[PDB]
Image (tube, coloured by chain):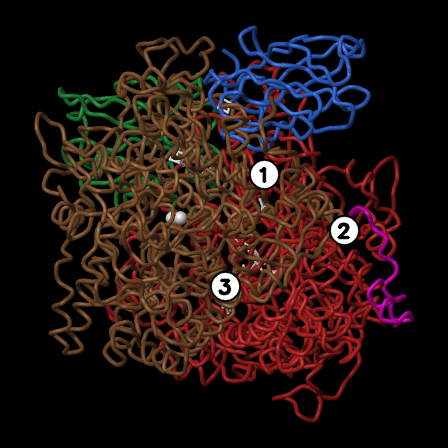
Chain colours: A brown, B red, C blue, D green
Amino acid sequence: AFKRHIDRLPIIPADAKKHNVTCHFCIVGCGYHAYTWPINKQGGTDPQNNIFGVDLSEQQQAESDAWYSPSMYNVVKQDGRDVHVVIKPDHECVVNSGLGSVRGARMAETSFSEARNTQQQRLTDPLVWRYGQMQPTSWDDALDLVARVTAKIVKEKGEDALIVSAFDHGGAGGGYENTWGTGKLYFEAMKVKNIRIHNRPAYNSEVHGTRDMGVGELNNCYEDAELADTIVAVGTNALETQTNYFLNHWIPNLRGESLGKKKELMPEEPHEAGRIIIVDPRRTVTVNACEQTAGADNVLHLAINSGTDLALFNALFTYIADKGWVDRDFIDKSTLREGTARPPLYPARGVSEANPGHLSSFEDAVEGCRMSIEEAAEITGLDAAQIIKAAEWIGMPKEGGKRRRVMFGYEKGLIWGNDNYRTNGALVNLALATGNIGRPGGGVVRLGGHQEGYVRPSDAHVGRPAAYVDQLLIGGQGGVHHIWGCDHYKTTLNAHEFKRVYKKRTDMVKDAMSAAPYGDREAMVNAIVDAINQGGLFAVNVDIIPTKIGEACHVILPAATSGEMNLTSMNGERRMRLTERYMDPPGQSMPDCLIAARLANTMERVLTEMGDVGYAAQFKGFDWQTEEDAFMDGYNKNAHGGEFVTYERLSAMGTNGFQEPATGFTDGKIEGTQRLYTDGVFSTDDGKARFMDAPWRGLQAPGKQQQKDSHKYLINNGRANVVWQSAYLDQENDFVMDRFPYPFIEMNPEDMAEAGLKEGDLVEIYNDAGATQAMAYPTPTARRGETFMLFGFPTGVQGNVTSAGTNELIIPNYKQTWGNIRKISDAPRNVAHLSFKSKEYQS
Amino acid sequence: AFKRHIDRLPIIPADAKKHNVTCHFCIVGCGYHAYTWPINKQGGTDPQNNIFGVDLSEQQQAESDAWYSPSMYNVVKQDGRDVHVVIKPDHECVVNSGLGSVRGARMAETSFSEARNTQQQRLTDPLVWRYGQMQPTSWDDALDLVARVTAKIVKEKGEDALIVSAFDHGGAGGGYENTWGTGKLYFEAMKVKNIRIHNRPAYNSEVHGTRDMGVGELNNCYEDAELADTIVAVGTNALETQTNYFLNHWIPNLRGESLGKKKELMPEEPHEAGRIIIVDPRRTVTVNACEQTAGADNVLHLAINSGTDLALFNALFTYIADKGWVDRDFIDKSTLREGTARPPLYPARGVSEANPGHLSSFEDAVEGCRMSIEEAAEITGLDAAQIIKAAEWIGMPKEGGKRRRVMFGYEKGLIWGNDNYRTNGALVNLALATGNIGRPGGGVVRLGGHQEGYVRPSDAHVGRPAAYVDQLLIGGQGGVHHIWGCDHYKTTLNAHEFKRVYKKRTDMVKDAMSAAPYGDREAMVNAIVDAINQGGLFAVNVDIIPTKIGEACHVILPAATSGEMNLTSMNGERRMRLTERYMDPPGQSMPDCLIAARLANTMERVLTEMGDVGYAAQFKGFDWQTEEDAFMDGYNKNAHGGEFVTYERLSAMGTNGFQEPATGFTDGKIEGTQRLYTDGVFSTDDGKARFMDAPWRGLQAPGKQQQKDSHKYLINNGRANVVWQSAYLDQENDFVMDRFPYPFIEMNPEDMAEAGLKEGDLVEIYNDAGATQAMAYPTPTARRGETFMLFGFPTGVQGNVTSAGTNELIIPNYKQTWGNIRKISDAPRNVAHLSFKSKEYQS
Amino acid sequence: AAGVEYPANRLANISELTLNEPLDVAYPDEDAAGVLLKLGTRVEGGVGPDGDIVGFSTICPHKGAPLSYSADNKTFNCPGHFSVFDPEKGGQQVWGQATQNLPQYVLRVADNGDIFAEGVDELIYGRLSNVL
Amino acid sequence: AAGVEYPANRLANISELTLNEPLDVAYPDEDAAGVLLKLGTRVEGGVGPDGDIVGFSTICPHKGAPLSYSADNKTFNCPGHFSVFDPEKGGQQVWGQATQNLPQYVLRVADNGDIFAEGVDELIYGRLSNVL
Ligand SMILES: Nc1nc2c(c(=O)[nH]1)N[C@H]1C(S)=C(S)[C@@H](COP(=O)(O)OP(=O)(O)OC[C@H]3O[C@@H](n4cnc5c(=O)[nH]c(N)nc54)[C@H](O)[C@@H]3O)O[C@H]1N2
Ligand code: F3S
Ligand code: F3S
Ligand code: FES
Ligand code: FES
Ligand SMILES: [Mo+4]
Ligand SMILES: [O]
Ligand SMILES: [O]
């Protein structure tokens, strides 16, 4: 087992500089503080010599504020000087109440440190492919090259020849400053159509369904998970993936701890401990933890067949509407009352690829969705009694006929699941029908991924459906590719084909570059353009590490992430915080928003020198010298309630921030919105919500049914608790990599026995899309025929076996994947030290 | 400036485990000790609680044994446990007398530590190109893949389709165990012809000249530098490159400190403080240091024109012979008296490409070499008075009529200099003529590079001249490449062209691999072989880090280096020591000799399975389990005196070891040989040394005169004191990279002004062979028109601008390089912190 | 003093321990709860004739809840937030919220059966120095 | 205590320093020779109104020979083995045999012009702890 052998830690002194810090990582947005103080000083164990006012000579008690793990401690540069830093979770933050997850609590140890040699992989200098390898250089040199190639291709081929891949998210590698910067470059200065997002290969929304219906996806507050009678948890593994929401808000509900709170806010009605329905094909540690906390009678795990959620929700909708277990006045008052006729191709297809579902009234939607318990039991593989029970836990009145309050929470099990638009809609139907939006203990919400931090100019030019970028790239289209803060090599769909083609096309430009003179820049630029014209691709990566896609790139631009800069974002409750800079960017690395600005300045200069003065002038408005300039040009001027928010005011509010949108500022407080839709006025022209007539139509995405019928196993995929995303930071973190050197593929012990495998064996997963590797992990809770592989992992990319299949709006259907499995090697020696024991807590 | 902020170090306790450690790095082979003790124990300041028996609560005085720098401390794995280690120089080692160079003294800090995060770049696992990227895997898998491809190719195409590049040297990344394992694999089991060495592109000697003359190039002892009247240092920058030999042995001579000992061991002649002739077109910190210690009147810096050494030596030989400043008795008794005939194509060309010069008697060599002072002054650019003065400093009898004792030391300025064979012989002529071989204060020796540790089967099948491997590879020939412990991307000649072609040929195999299924291994192997038949190359890297050439390779195998294994080698005095293992190999890394043996075993198995049982049996003789088994099969059975040497016996000799060859073993001591040739019996069949009739014939290598004529500056090249080799370890050492993030190119300040360059500017160096980058370092001592670029450096490779030109024996003429210089960028911000002051100590 | 000075403390005798049954102990002082445990098989950090006696802190490095031991599984389990540690593999967190594998004792068995602890390989919950 | 406890020692007053002439001091005790040096241009670790006052150990971190100062070049120079350190660039070893750039004092000027040293950024030659 990995052990740091760090016997003691420097003590935070009493005069240490305090900084407010939102977690770099997940949507929950747990509050932390970073405390820094000069190298060559320290606190003492006497109360007035440390920050805690506590005697550190004696053993602190459980949940102590006066302790931190070694992963919370580092040394970093700050204004050019080495300082001690501790990054420690805030007890006073209502999101987390001092919880720090396994990811967040390692922000310090995954920071860049020369003095203690952490994250020495971090990018420090611009790199350019020249003289036969990547070579460091100046910013002026590298941007120049990028601008000139980009400018020439775009002048000769139009802006369609510029392909962009970029984060649209919040937190580290995202945020309002950084989404504004990149957005402004590509959508204000330019009209880039062939742009895709970090997690999906087109410029779309994850949840067009709920938005079209008028219900924006983050409509509740985290307190609603404490107040609900029933939590409906769809396609979430929240203990692993939205950890501290689960622990600090859901658990008190299930345990009975929030009964006093329920009673005070909602007398006039009966309350019991929270019950929970979990819709997930896989029995997860979330399921186990729910059972251990609430008892098994209070947990309904619907272990559905992969991709059958829509059938289940349509049955639930049918049964609840027939019983009349609905909020009649919410429907009359707040939903669309005049139905409208089905489009001609229904139920198989919508009016067009742009509208996969039919929006209409409650009663039209019920008749459209109508599915009996017996049909949904066939499709979902659930028992009829399980479906009836869940309709009861969602819809049945409580004693005295009072409305059952239900928080409906969904994430990637649904969004990357089958028929995203219709499944999304059919779940929103359940919430609208039961009046569970805009009310305490309600919500139909994304549980979320990254934090949120989106402000950009109009994307109207993009279209709906937008262009499927990976397919343009695979098919030889496009000339120049700017990649910001994502790594398709590890995380796109159909990733094996993507890599083969991306290498080949970038190699053409590599070979031309190696053979041409660099010091003569015009000749290098022309040699690149000639290669692009023959089918090559010139590629530029803006990142904080050497990425996998980066190995194909021609120019790499070093970025500064959260904490090295100021950053704003909101959590899954709309809670906007400012993370206050506490350290310097490594070497010459620079905030993304300022990278975009310097790039815009360079485009202007270059286009001017080419004599295209008109095009050059589109790139003005980028005079920003610090990230706050981007905040003010973007968020402050464009978000609803943006006028009320500044860095100074945000900082004053601390880690609790406020909930967006801001409604005003009085008495040094930004006033916010606790829940959305409290007045029953939805996000449509007429203020009414729509229901969705959304009939089940099987596996919707191309090739999926053929992939299921022709391979042995389900290759379910997703997150591990210990791993953050594509392990970009984690690959230089021994604690994480000592645990999983290879990605795990969870397999039922009997399935393993049948296939001739033993724990730790390295196996090839393969199908029609490609092939990859993973380490067999015996998982007694796994159903026969169903495996789960860790996604995004550098030592075994799951995406290689995901097909190209998307829904009509180009949403990638990663969860419905099937494959074969065969052995590559006996368990390697580098895996002999691992535990292969169950991940479930035992009582 | 880089600062560790390490305020204090754990004290070595009285009971630490002591290990004999030869420096990993240069020829000098400084002796060290590695002290390990358990994590969680420590020494204290009282004498009884530390290894020194000194009170460490008191400041220590200059040259204290009871101190160590932060770079000599780390924590490492040893038998699976974390231990403190200190690796510190040995006061008692006669080689260094407690000196640790800037490189030696950072052995601990450049070791792998999970607990302190040093050298996290070290390879831990075999890697194979599959599924779009490098992926980690098991030894059994990776070796099976290597052997199947290698075996299929050799069976279809012959052994000539296997190309090999390997170390032939000693110390870390070489040594007697490792050279034997690799040599047995490729020269016993196989007869590989197309093998090159780490520093030169064919299987040749660096010094065929001196060896053909019967004078093995390491024929003296280090004491001889203390004892000479005159040192002649040719093409060496010993203060930077043979640092501790220079400081512990040359300096005492120059300072007069060795007079006592001189007059002790050689009474019956006069002794004065040693004088030194330095033959080097560049004024180095070596020249400066010599002047500062001995006085400028005792240092003669012959600042010759690049590549004109031969004309100087032939003039000196002529003048000295004419004056009769020769050792007549040594010449009559110990050298060829035979008359001979110059070959038909003399003087332009030898008898064949195998023999570029003509071996003769003293008298025929004098007449063949004959060159006037005036003609050599014309060629070398030196004054007549300087050449006459050098001839006196070498040949003029001392006061009694007594023979002047002279140590001739040479290194890469000569060896990678012009007309290697003739120039080597012409220098040896001087030492032969003056009887300065086999005698105290004498010698004509390599000053060396790496330590030495060669023992291998006969190389007779290789031929002479041997195959020019880079040219085979660049021309599309060969099928499989095994690369061990060298990185041509940084260090071969004509490296820009090498890299363009190497990338292209390996890409072909990569593209085939990524499209074939790995789990059907026979299909993988066939795809690889087909790609090879189309012109591809399959390339396997054995190394300790991800290398530059490694980025083109398809399999990577992780090696363990000195200290992680036991290792034997000798220094430039033939002093053989055993480095005793003190730590574990990182992850699954294994010593090179055992990798070779497992590769041998896998070839036996794979060939057996193919039905080629007779060929398979040639791969027996590799049952080794530990590196000592390769020592015993190699050195012990094959070196002269081998039977006397074992690990246990070496260990007892400590860091002083013995000088090879061993003559015997008595009373617990391996007995050795202080100097070679003390009886006047040389390494030829008849025992007589030959002189060399070796006439000047200009710049010998193809294209060199044209390169010089058509480009503005000399691009001299070579080492820096702070940097070790291609910075394989140094690139994750902040002390080194903070000093020089780019390779420097030394430039005369007027040369800078006239080219519009400022200190730190990033410049392109370009010519017919290619282009590269470096950072301009203003250097007042540099001559107008003459620049010097650090060689082998990852962030700007000098080799790119060296042409393919070799001598007839395929010796790479790196030092004669001319090219143009132009600016790429203004000083980048990442060099703003650098000092650009003179490297020369000021009094 | 550059490193923590750990006391060498007697904890129990090889004879006091029954197979697969933890025994409560404390190290390096009375306020730091732990166990010894004899596991029946050779393991990482294990001492004794069978190389199977290990010692661990039993205070969760996440937030301090005392860990329970499941005998059927040979794991430590946290009632706070569901962490699981494997003392058969150096205390590796199998699944959990701590950023540390379970602090494990450097143990020595004396010629007379006595069991000393003289080290811990991670930072114990609730103290910024393992020796206070 | 986890780190070294440096004393905040008064070395001299800003008024005692003449441009480019070192003033011999000692820090963090009397056996650890160093100098304060006013350089006439703002530099790394430099204090005082012009940002140009630096403090260094003048004991060679290689083998301990006392360093000489060249006023013409503004460098420390070692007569032991020819090392050169640049006090205008944080003590950077321009060329030399140490594995350390020159240990530099963390300095502070009080309102009366008094110069204190409160730390050192590298390990002083001849001691295994900068504070003995
Ligand atoms: N610090 C350090 N020391 C090392 C090494 C290292 O990487 N770093 N590597 C080691 C290795 S492998 C080697 S091979 C040795 C190399 O040791 P050296 O040969 O001493 O070092 P170089 O800098 O390669 O070249 C030495 C001198 O040759 C001069 N020179 C160039 N052209 C000519 C010429 O035409 N004639 C003459 N007479 N001189 C010329 C250069 O100006 C230079 O000063 O050093 C070893 N020692
Ligand atoms: S700590 Fe960070 S990772 Fe998610 S649960 Fe809290 S935000
Ligand atoms: S310390 Fe090492 S690098 Fe050479 S001078 Fe001595 S062997
Ligand atoms: S206290 Fe143990 S898992 Fe949180
Ligand atoms: S003592 Fe200063 S250079 Fe060696
Ligand atoms: Mo996501
Ligand atoms: O996400
Ligand atoms: O060499």
Question: Which quarter shows the C terminus of chain B?
Answer: top left
Asked if the beta carbon under badge 1 is closer than 8 A to the nearest atom of ligand 4, the reply is no
Q: Chain of mark 3?
A: A
Depth check: B668 or A265 in front? Answer: A265
Question: Residue B583 placed where, x, y %?
Answer: 67, 38
**Mark 3 vs mark 1, CA separation in Å:** 27 Å
Q: Which residue is mark 2?
A: A756
Question: Residue D18 placed where, x, y %?
Answer: 18, 32
Depth check: A63 or A830 in front? Answer: A63
Q: Which residue is mark 1?
A: A739
**Mark 2 vs mark 1, CA separation in Å:** 24 Å
Which of discs 2 and 1 lies nearer the camera? The answer is 2
Q: Chain of mark 2?
A: A
Q: Which residue is mark 3?
A: A494
Q: Residue at x 14, y 33 (%)?
A: A649
**In the depicted structure, whether residue A258 falls above or below residue B120:** above
Decide whether residue B617 is among the magenta residues.
yes
Asked if the beta carbon under badge 3 is closer than 8 A to the nearest atom of ligand 6, the reply is no
Q: Chain of mark 1?
A: A
First of labels 3, 1 by sequence position: 3
**Mark 2 vs mark 3, CA separation in Å:** 28 Å
Question: Which quarter shows the N terminus of chain B?
Answer: top left
Question: Residue B364 placed where, x, y %?
Answer: 70, 82
